[PDB]
Image (tube, coloured by chain):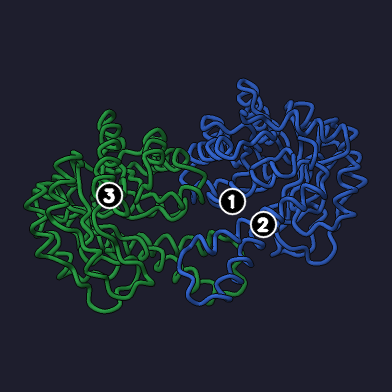
Chain colours: A green, B blue
Amino acid sequence: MPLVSMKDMLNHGKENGYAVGQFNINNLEFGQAILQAAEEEKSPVIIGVSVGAANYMGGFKLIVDMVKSSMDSYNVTVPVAIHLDHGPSLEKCVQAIHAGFTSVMIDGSHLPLEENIELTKRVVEIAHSVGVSVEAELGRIGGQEDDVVAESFYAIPSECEQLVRETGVDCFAPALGSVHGPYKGEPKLGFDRMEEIMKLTGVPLVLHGGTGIPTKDIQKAISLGTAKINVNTESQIAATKAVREVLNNDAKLFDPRKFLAPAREAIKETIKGKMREFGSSGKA
Amino acid sequence: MPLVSMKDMLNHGKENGYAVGQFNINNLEFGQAILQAAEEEKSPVIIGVSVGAANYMGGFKLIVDMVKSSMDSYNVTVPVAIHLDHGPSLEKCVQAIHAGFTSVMIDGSHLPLEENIELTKRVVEIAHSVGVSVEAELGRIGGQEDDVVAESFYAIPSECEQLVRETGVDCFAPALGSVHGPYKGEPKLGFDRMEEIMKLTGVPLVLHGGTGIPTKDIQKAISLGTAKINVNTESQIAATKAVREVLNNDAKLFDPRKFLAPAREAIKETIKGKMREFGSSGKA
């Protein structure tokens, strides 16, 4: 019943026209919500961890132990991967792998293409010694404060062809108009480039900034080889709304469990919704 | 640093005129705050766990795993016990011990003396097979519901003498006016009876209902052999006020960690104050 890499689940997704969601563990409470969503939807799932979330929770190894303890406690039978989101360095990837992560994203996208390929290739060499999956990136994900995405931040498909051939990465994140947080207007996704990058790379693609992409775009991204979609802030927002609401309705409430339990129910419903939109439901 | 039973820490307390606090882990990140409070105060500490809290967090084994993982990642050097609070049955004591609990309270105080004695003796037999410490009770702790504490609820000292002698428990909780949650007014602790119970039993005594027990009352309980004092609702009340405040002062906050972080800080400061008040600061 144990943890798995993203390799088999993203290939099964690419083969059958669906996407696995990655949902980031914000804090320890979230972890349980993500697993019971996946268990209830008979969905594979990817638990994303940021370096910042890891610092908040007490490290990579505590998060692995707690996901493994939770899978045991809730009888989780669906495929679960633990993935380092936007890993900044070889050192952090090694540390995440040593802690028991099953997957890493080495984000070399801020580097020159050759430096990115070198760094990525070194992480792959490590990861593939021990059954770990690797994600890499080209181009740049919109920041919340950036307004519309500069055309210069879009991945160039011929660079994507080279990076994936030269590194051996299992899956690839081309930045094609994605943003972190609320889309300012319509999402401007480069579907023609996505199709090219799909065709040139032959690996499962990854869509960052899945919060606010409508079923039309999601369904289009999946048709063009997207097998992994990252949804983070939608869950954070559903959690905090649920807390604000129970505090505002009941001034006497003093047991944190009475505001954490509604938070958990909201996170779980958000995630089940996405597992249903992505077509991961019933695939486990 | 391994977990330890309550045996040595409560003896050191009794012998030097201080008490060890029990702080109940309400949810997974209360645990962090309790261990950080202990480490910073160089204090022993007891992490209390209810059956209700274990049900919320995913069971006894997951809680023990998480406490050990946290101890490991925050380099905890102080003595830490994990104690089953008001254990309702031999079955729950066994399930807690099997999961790695170092201490149980078997609460037979609603049964006839002779049944409480027999139940307690059976749990001691099990617990003392594997270096687990045991707490028992006579008389009954009130609730904010019934206000004034009936005299029929106070432990009878000759019954305390018989139960402790017949069972071999390590420590003992006499209900002597304690209440869970807030006091109607001033607490009516039976200190003459407490002193008698200390002399006739010769084991460290436990004070339940420590939330909102004035300082003089606490200091007097320690002087008459209370070496363990349970504080729960104070910490719940401090976490929830920090959460209300931060959400009230920022309408656009959406990242749960931004409300969790000051909750953790309010808990830790609450628990540090208790550790100075009981005198366990500096004792580790």
Residue B246's quadrant in the figure?
Answer: bottom right
Q: Disc 1 designates what residue?
A: B30
Q: Amino acid at mark 1?
A: Phe
Image quadrant holding the N terminus of chain A, namely top left
Q: Amino acid at mark 3?
A: Val
Q: Residues within 10 Å of mark 2 (few under 14, many from 20)?
A: many
Dots 2 and 1 on the same chain: yes
- Residue A174 placement, left or right of A237: left
Q: Secondary structure at mark 2?
A: helix
Q: Disc 2 designates what residue?
A: B235
Residue at far top of view: B129
Q: Residues within 10 Å of mark 3 (few under 14, many from 20)?
A: many
Q: CA distance from mark 1 to mark 3?
A: 27 Å
- Residue B172 placement, left or right of A109: right
User: Residue shown at 34%/41% (left/top)?
Assistant: A75
Q: Residues within 10 Å of mark 1 (few under 14, many from 20)?
A: many
Q: Amino acid at mark 2?
A: Ser
Q: Secondary structure at mark 3?
A: strand
Q: Secondary structure at mark 1?
A: helix
